[PDB]
Amino acid sequence: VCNTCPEKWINFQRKCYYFGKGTKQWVHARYACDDMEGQLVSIHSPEEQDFLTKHASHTGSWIGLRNLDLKGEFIWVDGSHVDYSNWAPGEPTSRSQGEDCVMMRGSGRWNDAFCDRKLGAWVCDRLATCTP
Ligand SMILES: [Ca+2]
């Protein structure tokens, strides 16, 4: 039974989530999550997405999706590929033009963006720990 989360993190299913605040570009958020022993959030189901939207900032948040090698394939920071997606209409933009980072809007839907864009929120996740 794995639902144990650290103080300030919120459990959903087998993961823990931290809804961060404070102005950060994508890689800044990446390291903020890393320094908290987590990583920018990966999303693999509509149930997970719905949970995130419920707790997420109205003004948009960095998540852990990025065009890894700059060549057009978006990969989650945890290493996994996209199965579930929640792209906003028309996203991602059908051009390789250096908008390699993904944010989640107030609606929960995703759009690509310049990685140096400063957003006011960012979400981390980590595995919940378990009772023996
Ligand atoms: Ca776009």
Image: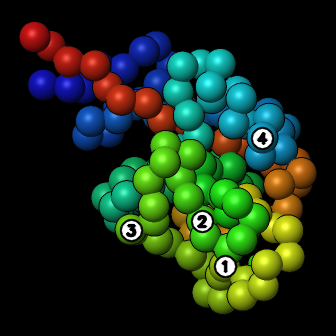
Quarter of the image where the C terminus is located: top left
User: Who comes first in sequence, dot 2 or dot 3?
Assistant: 2
Quarter location, residue 2: top left
Residue at 89 percent across and 51 percent down: it is 116
> Quadrant for ligand 1?
bottom right
- Which mark, residue 83? 3
Q: Amino acid at mark 3?
A: Asp
Query: Where residue 84 sits in the image (x, y, percent)?
Result: 39, 68
Residues at marks 1 and 4, CA–CA distance in whole angstroms: 19 Å
Do the residues bearing badges 1 and 2 touch, measured as CB atoms within 8 Å? yes
- Whether 26 is drawn above or below 68: the answer is above
**Mark 2 surroundings: few (<14), some (14-19) or many (≥20) residues within 10 A:** many
Residues at marks 1 and 2, CA–CA distance in whole angstroms: 10 Å
Do the residues bearing badges 4 and 3 touch, measured as CB atoms within 8 Å? no
Q: Amino acid at mark 1?
A: Pro
Q: Amino acid at mark 4?
A: Val
In the image, 28: left or right of 1?
right
User: Who comes first in sequence, dot 4 or dot 3?
Assistant: 4
- Which mark, residue 92? 1
Residue bearing the label numbered 2? 74
Residue at 70 percent across and 60 percent down: it is 69
Between 48 and 32, which is closer to the camera in this rendering? 32
Residues at marks 2 and 3, CA–CA distance in whole angstroms: 11 Å
In the image, 24: left or right of 60?
right
Query: Where residue 95 sits in the image (x, y, percent)?
Result: 78, 85
Residue at 83 percent across and 39 percent down: it is 24
